[PDB]
Length: 156
RNA sequence: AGUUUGGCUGGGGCGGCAUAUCUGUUACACGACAACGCAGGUGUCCUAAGGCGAGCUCAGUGGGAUCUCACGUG
Ligand SMILES: [Mg+2]
Image 1 (spheres, rainbow, N blue to C red):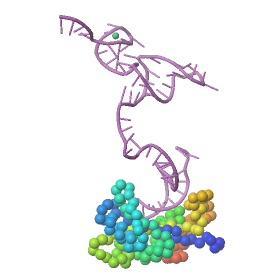
Image 2 (cartoon, rainbow, N blue to C red):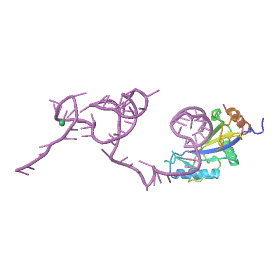
Image 3 (cartoon, chains in turn purple, brown):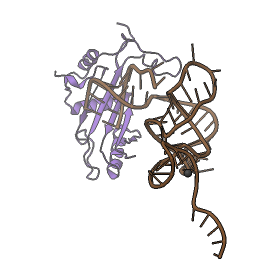
Image 4 (tube, rainbow, N blue to C red):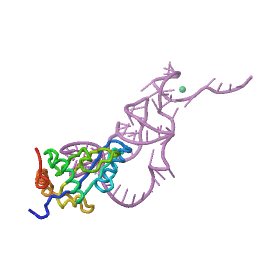
C-alpha cells in the first residue's frame, strides 16, 4: 500500500543471565563485547546478576542472520507476541562460529527483536507525545508474514 | 539527735497515668467542649534522610526469551 508502511527491525536485545557476580560475569561481559563490537551494561536485581546490550542498525541485521542460521531458520508459532515482536535463544556461543578459547568456556544467550513502522517516534519524543494509532500498530499476523517473506520457515 | 517518707482516684490500698505533650473519633456541618472514654504515638533518628538544577515514573496487570512491549488518576 503506502510507501511508508514497511516493517523494519527496530532493535535487537541480547541478554545473558548467568545468575552470579565475579569472574563469570567478567567473561560474559567480554564475550558480548566481541559479539556485537559495542560496550555492554550490567543489570542487577545490588547482586549483579546479568549482563545485556541492545543493538540497532545494520549490525543488528547481521547478528540476527547469524542467530537464525544456528536456529535452522525455523521458529515456533507461539514464539511470537501480539505486540509484534518475537524472540528465541541459543545455547552455545561456539556454535555461533566464534573461536573457542579454553578460558571463557561456553555460554548461552537470549535474542529479542522488535519490529515496527516509521511512525513510532511520536510516542517517544519529549514534546507533544501522543499515541501511535490502531492501524499503524504492527499485529502478530503481520509479524509472522514478515518472517515468512524474509528468512522463511515457521511451524505452528 | 533532727527531719522526710508525691499526686490523681466512682472511699483508701494494690494496679494504671487520664501528671508535660501529637493524630483520628467522641464533638451536635464557624470556633470552643468532659470522663481511670475509644484506636494509636512522643523524650528519638538524619552531612544527608538538609539546599538546588536536570532526567525519569510508581504499585500492579497482560503478551513474549533478569530482558522487551502495551496499559496503568496514584
Ligand atoms: Mg491521695
